[PDB]
Image (cartoon, rainbow over all chains, first blue to last red; front, top):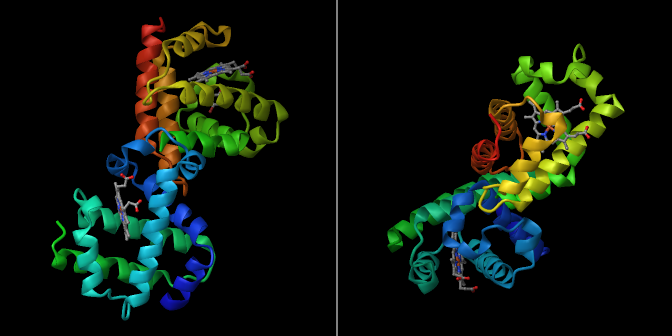
Length: 137
Length: 137
Ligand code: HEM
Ligand code: HEM
Ligand SMILES: COc1cc(Br)ccc1O
């Protein structure tokens, strides 16, 4: 289930983080509006760009902690508030997060490794709701 | 995005070339008049012929070179000119290329792969414009 999936992802976190974020960027190419430095780069080139590697690593380290602190895929309100208060996220809306989780769930379903994709779908929806309550536009 | 799509296509160049060319020929059966040596054969009959695989791979390799040399999905005028001046392309008009890219985009949208179909649509339109500028009727 969801808790085991956190352990699966953490066991190969760099690769899963890269894979999933690339699946997000390739499913929704207009999302590069927030990452102007990623334009004109293949997946392999992005993986060898320091700011892509460092951002994706931080995203997934923190996302796994938020998932780990959740109860039944409902994140702590404090985790949603922290994400809202992040200065580097001033231009983001809940739709950016929604799209990330749609891409993540699709990636899990296509993987062939026993992920509980329905729980990740609920987690993404519950994170979006919590972000809204915490003040994200 | 577009650059990643070039890498996806190049990774399995011949297979994609055959499936896209077949998609084109089947969507536009009259276009086979330019390909008199491929008439009267099913998709699998064509794929079994080494000359079909060789032809499609050579075509698609050049298409990927033109795509990779493009800037923001605008091909180089010199590449458009090469395509206009090729002896094998005598008598073609831009409508032949418009149909190819319609079929290519439709194939991408129907595929399970995460192609940036909007960029390929724009690339096809910009290639048609560039072919006109390079002297194709
Ligand atoms: C759980 C989800 C996310 C987490 C934990 C997260 C975390 C972070 C952190 C810690 C930074 C600081 C810079 C760094 O550490 O490299 C950052 C920056 C940034 N984030 Fe995220 N983020 C998340 C989702 C997103 C999404 C979905 C987007 C856009 C669709 C986004 C866009 C950005 C941008 C543009 C920066 C600036 C980085 C740069 O300029 O290179 N973030 N994020
Ligand atoms: C960007 C698009 C295109 C590229 C890069 C391209 C490139 C090429 C190349 C490299 C060849 C030589 C292939 C070989 O060695 O067998 C070729 C041949 C040919 N192409 Fe194109 N082509 C394109 C579009 C088209 C279109 C739209 C048509 C007609 C609908 C067309 C009709 C032909 C024909 C009739 C030949 C000769 C085939 C034969 O020898 O029997 N091409 N093309
Ligand atoms: C429309 O022309 C072609 C397109 C592809 Br893709 C492969 C072979 C061709 O002749």
